[PDB]
Length: 131
RNA sequence: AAACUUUCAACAACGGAUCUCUUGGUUCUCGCAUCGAUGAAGAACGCAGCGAAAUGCGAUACGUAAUGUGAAUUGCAGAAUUCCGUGAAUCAUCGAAUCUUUGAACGCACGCGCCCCUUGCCAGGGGGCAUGCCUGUUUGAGGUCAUU
Image 1 (cartoon, rainbow, N blue to C red):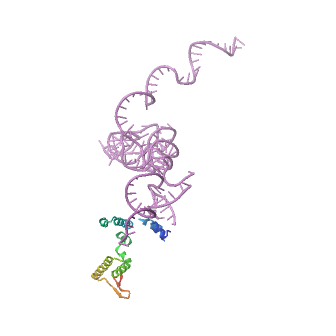
Image 2: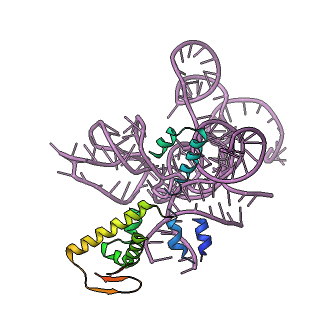
Image 3: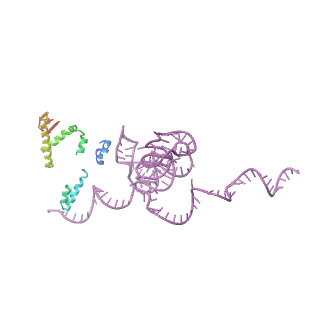
């Protein structure tokens, strides 16, 4: 069997289900060198012109109910960031997402269990936590 | 004498010489430019029911695809055909396919490796990986200049 390091370099796992999986993140690296070239040129207009995961979601979760498997960690991370070198815009977006989720939950009032704890106020709809 | 040597008329054998002819050769004149990595010429193996040569064909193998003709092919068997019909010919045209192994011959050589993928540790199935050079994209390394 191909080792994890060897498989990653080529791209313990089954080779049958990994070889076919070899098929914009790599292309984005060119933007760094283009920006460096623009900086070297000393003009910012070209830099401004240069400046101007749905696919993975479906395969991981082919159906909406399947999202519940990872929704625990998803909500945990989102709520942790909502209260936390992360940019302020990322924090604001995470807080807005959590606020919208809470508003929708309150609209339907789909809550069954709660538990105030030292770690945080636990909740159940699916279980989720907020600090 | 018979037998046997020799000249000649007739009869009986060789060979195709003479005569007649040819889907032939040679020579003259006229129109055109038409080989090849999108794989040339050439060589080997197979293909028709029966097959020596020639021609055609490449496991779709004396052919497959398409149009015209309209009732065949023929040495033998065999097929039919609704033949008033989108339909037979070993017919003609031929623009669409297949195109075995070699061969400029092209994975590495003087047997024999790799990407791919697939339908079921492992495999069938399908295309490629030769060298010289031109344009473009990607990565890596090294000389100049800048670095308050």
